[PDB]
Length: 121
RNA sequence: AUCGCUUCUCGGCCUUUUGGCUAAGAUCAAGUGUAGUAUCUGUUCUUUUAAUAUCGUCCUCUACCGAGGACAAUAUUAA
Image (cartoon, rainbow, N blue to C red):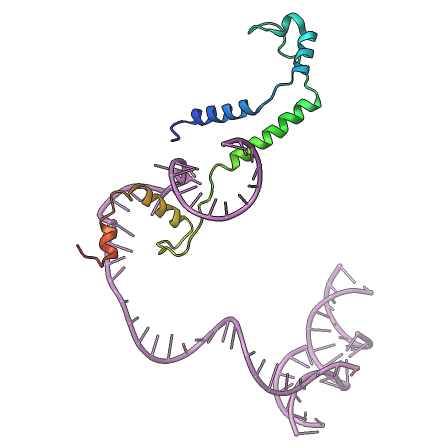
């Protein structure tokens, strides 16, 4: 179940962070260029220095577009059958009756049987 | 088994949805006839007399101009 906005974030982060692959060439290049400060503390100096080249920002933009697509596929539309006896006259009435069947559907299980058998019992 | 695309079923999001209050706010009813508007169907224009109304000249008043009177036919409709 859902239970939190942070647990779905954590699941989504584990997915993205397992999908990524690091490049050791760029890593060792920047390590050899930066030297002493490549293992920084909270307070070293480099906060206002990095300028990423075009390939890095292109990779970030493509990854973020894929992430936006994965987010937009979150609520899949359930298929609409017209064989069920419809009990709504609007477009919002159908979804409100669906919410009523979600919440009160466990309790109001005898009266629907009474209705379908002819208002008896 | 694994990765990808396409049918098919289903779960979770679906308050993303009923946006107040008072004396359930109160009450609980109709027929006929005319007038107006809209739609549909059918078919038309351009190239004498009766009634009503009112530019020129002359006269008077006041400071060429203005007002008032009179006179000279004109317009409409029908055969």
